[PDB]
Length: 518
Ligand SMILES: [Mn+2]
Ligand SMILES: [Mn+2]
Ligand SMILES: [Mn+2]
Picture 1 (cartoon, rainbow, N blue to C red):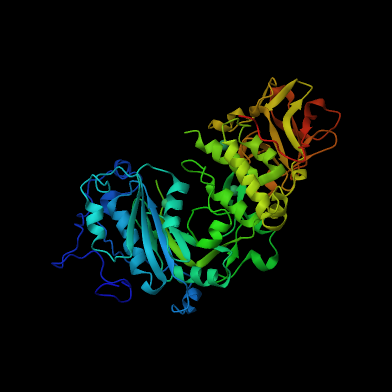
Picture 2 (cartoon, rainbow, N blue to C red):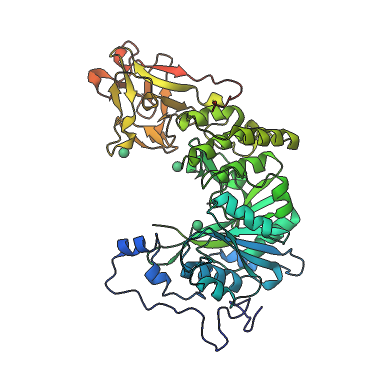
């Protein structure tokens, strides 16, 4: 703690020079004649004119529910933590305001260090061979602020791993490079991990508008879509939770099948013991789901802490497919579904190093993905593959044509009727738990009686029954879909009408999933 430590400046007055002036020249108010789209382009998604005009010691509103402030933490018994902030070409104002925010709002007793990881930035203000603005300014901050560099941009996993391997505290908390904290953001995480070292605890994320920089209030539980990305519990999925967990208290810690932002705190030893990150994940993407799956299956738990809140400025290669293939290692027989949803790709997912993580999985004794679905994410639409009874073409023999979803990538999300070619654009799947008829390449798109695709919702407005006669019956209206006239229209159900009889391939996937060759 430097000179001037008090409430709102727990590490002292930051960024002040020997003569007493701040070490950072704040910009004047943004021009009155400033076009936002250009300003956002110049700022890489941020309003830099405004950010550069705001103070690094910026007050933020307490986003915590009032009840969170009725809690006490004994800082002498909590374990120290190491805050890690990775950044690639983060502008000075947002990076240092993130640092100031943490230092000002984190007691020195529980903050071992603050590690800034430069993941190969190229801006002149950061470079080793640049103008030295950043390094010079760090000299005006507590010595517990460190800077470490990657000479080449590694990506999410590589840069975080370097920061984690460099942290000395028993707990590390990973943040973003464009954040502001609510008060007492860290104390909840430390207390929860001290009581059980196997818990990875995520703060809840509020928002900072990228144009106005207004502070905005942010759920908790996250599922995943078969496109292999996290997705919040929809209304119909929280309705499947036990009644005690549907509407949880704001102070309650709540479990989550999946992580999103990448902001979390963990016991360093347990993190490495449970696999850390798969350091073959390239650039960015999906490392949060592989972590979430592996964590739960190998003895960990993932929790969200609503009394721990961080503001996040939301913005306005061939590695992405690889990252998904490697994540499918942890999905056992369900990878067949995931693999078909992302287009049956055949990439070089680096099989040699993935065998090693498979051998690691057994040696550790991790549980199965079926166990994960039945015990961690039983509210999902697909808990067993038996929940997807049809996958293939929806074909009307009478006219000799198939349902064509190629238009889901067109403004008019109209489903069509075309000669069958067997490609993915003519392949549909059925989720029986919700009656959804979707194309295999998007489980967020659902067939409507309008003959159009729209965003799936777990309601009666998307429920279809596939009858034993072959009819697609919209349950709400009890009408059936007909291909009469090469047009999609709803009609009275009548199993003698061949224009409303469809064939749909049953989905009987193998007991285990074999990876495609390279
Ligand atoms: Mn971010
Ligand atoms: Mn949704
Ligand atoms: Mn549409």
